[PDB]
Every structure is written in structure tokens, then in C-alpha cells.
Amino acid sequence: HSTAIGRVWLSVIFIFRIMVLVVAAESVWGDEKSSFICNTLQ
Amino acid sequence: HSTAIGRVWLSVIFIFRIMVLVVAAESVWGDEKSSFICNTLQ
Image (tube, rainbow over all chains, first blue to last red; front, side, top):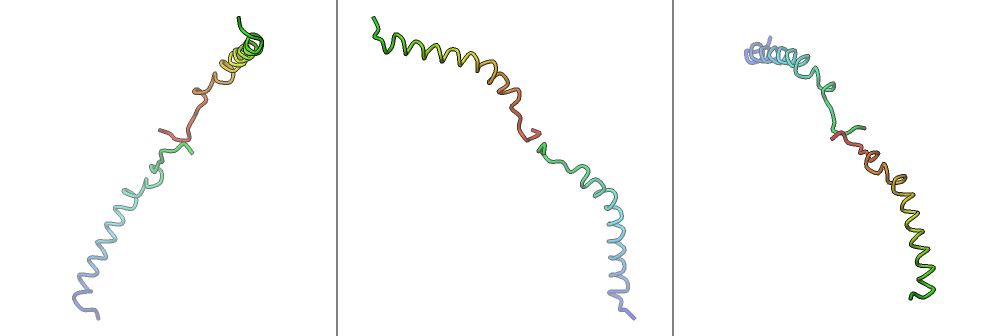
């Protein structure tokens, strides 16, 4: 029922976001807090 | 040749400063820098 601009392009871009997020979830943001250190001793 | 106000009182006060400084030199100020710590990790 959808037109061509959303049937193809929107779905592909959504899959692109899914794949990029999966790649960047465990890898880029895996050590976001463990390696987040501050210069203070508190 | 000195008068009474400096022959007795001034000398005694000077000795008082000597004794107090000797007591407070190694004891009070002995760990002035070794125990001087800062909250930073730098």
C-alpha cells in the first residue's frame, strides 16, 4: 500500500540504522563508562 | 650596659622563642609536606 519513496528508500535507511547501531553498540559504546575516568581521586 | 627591660625581659622572651621554635620545628612542622595531600590524582 506504500509508495516507492517509503517502500524501498525508507526501509533500506532503517536497515542501515539497525546495522550501524548493532556495530556501534557493543564496540564503540561498550567501554563508555568503564574507561570513563576523571582526574580527581574522589 | 643594657637596662633592666632588655637585660632580663627581652632575653627571657628570646629564650622562650628559641625553646618554642625547637619544640615546634621537628614535631609540628616535621610532616608539613609529607602529609600534605591533595584531592587530585594529578
